[PDB]
Image (tube, rainbow over all chains, first blue to last red; front, side):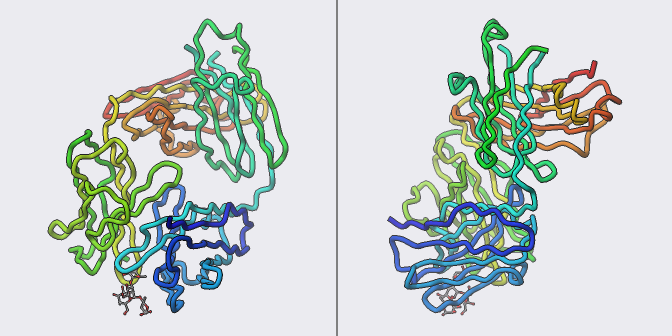
Length: 211
Length: 212
Ligand SMILES: C[C@@H]1O[C@@H](O)[C@H](O)[C@H](O)[C@H]1O[C@H]1O[C@H](CO)[C@@H](O)[C@H](O[C@H]2O[C@H](C)[C@H](O)C[C@H]2O)[C@@H]1O[C@H]1O[C@H](CO)[C@H](O)[C@H](O)[C@H]1O
């Protein structure tokens, strides 16, 4: 039907430049505007600008004019946004949306994540979280980049698991996961979290031991 | 430039009508501001809902309508469905910029409210060995999904060193969030009581531990 396909995840260093792109499907590219939206972690949404491929009219947010170049190739039905002189404040999910008269985005692309960081690939330090039903946890601390996958007892413990979203602390991520099991069950039944960090082929298992 | 203001959170039950408003710091919203409403559902799923003050976007249910009520733009959902639980943003075309409001979290009560299960974990030995100490507070199974988390070290409010995640939807449609207090092992040793206080629907839950 209408589809707005976006490019994937970008990892960039401070000072660099990136080019992100959006392909149209299901409509006449030339008759509509392509707008770009920035969504910060929690800083709401900000409109970056818009381009009309039919005549390449562009509109820009004043705040972003100095570092953004918006373009479109009609032959390829693709719009591009180039961002320059990146700083960690440009880390956000960017969306391209389809617009027209009186509106900027009836159909939305899926979002392309950009992280700007000078950090290096760092493996997680995994720590067991014992109390001393009972809730056990694993702290997965200090890894870069995303993601890590956490399982409990090699996937056999799937009920009662909560894995929380990562926070950035200093310039590395920290994440935790918990599992709740019947009291009787622990310690007789061994509970282990298994943490994989693909970028550094880190795989580590941590058995939870009562304190 | 101009500031666009929306309610921060509204709650309704299935089948009721609820109205969300969007206003500008220049006084009135007009037709020339082309008020837009979009919906944000989990995992960055956005849907256009209303464009140009009152046009439903393609395939939006007729229970969604946009109007200007007085000097404000407003979105009304007549007969709210459990699936309308989402964040709603309005934006206004002003000075050739689309300017966004901060969004309204709408809870549409499709199940009973549930209080948070809070769990506070102490630092592990292995981490204290690195000269760091991180306390972990997990908050799960709360519904509505809006909570505030406060940390106290020997009764004093903590203002630096804690991190809290935004509430994520559990698969059972309740919500979960975690908070971290990070200190050096040195500092952790100068204090005895540690508290994670979570307020949800005007009630506080406190989990406290003592270094010792
Ligand atoms: C598509 C059109 O192409 C040329 O004619 C010229 O470059 C125009 O600037 C350009 O777009 C303006 O005109 C059309 C008229 O139908 C509007 O639909 C456009 O507005 C839509 O897209 C922008 C980016 C916003 O999302 C708001 C949408 O309505 C756009 O309008 C803007 O420019 C004209 C200039 O004549 C006028 O000032 C409008 O008030 C302004 O919104």
